[PDB]
Image 1 (tube, rainbow over the protein chains, first blue to last red):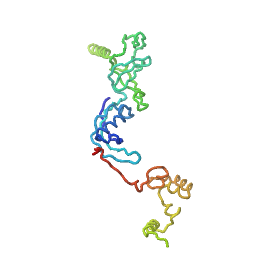
Image 2: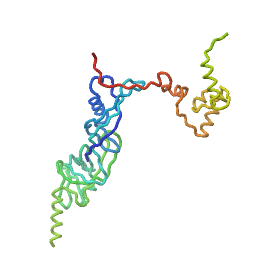
Image 3: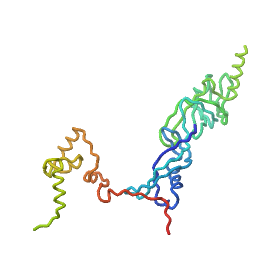
Image 4: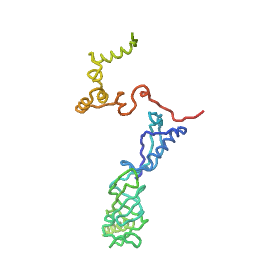
Length: 189
Length: 93
């Protein structure tokens, strides 16, 4: 889930951008370096916001480009294990369903879709419960729980995320309403 | 009849008498008291110095000239001690 992180960092500013002010040059270098990458501890680097303080450059032998201590805010989205997720199903597959949780997509296994048995109907390439007569189709809006996060590399595409859907308080909003109706009925009896 | 400046002689003598005793300039003296492992191993006895350094687990902080040459990093002498700083916005006249 989205958050703002203030990070201190050293920026290698090449001689070709010596003309512009240090703030914009540091902003650009951080856009090229951090933006669009996955970090193991904070999530997905989405957008560099702004730089507050930039230090004077240090010339080190070998390159001639200036190195500056910088302070900046990065808008980063962090998935957290065992939390709640609001999203829509981007697509479905026989092994699992893809749930849009933000910058990256999550996977809901068919064994975690329903307590009831499910079958992958190929007529519309959609899921359908055996006895509940419920169904999932592309574009449906559902609520699920994140249960597993895996991070291979800094590429956001490769890292995968798996969710759960059977547990109480989750499901399609219509099913949530039906469960609320059942709760009201059992409270009234 | 050879003319050498007194200051060089003073430097050599002061380095020779820096430990409170007069000690040689060779492998059993000033060189043998160098802290850097690689600097000592480069001079004369090499396998003995490396084996004894591995025995005691000595660390080479790379504060000298010889080892920085061996690894291929700037030596801390002459232009190697100059730290440079620069204000970024440059405006040609």
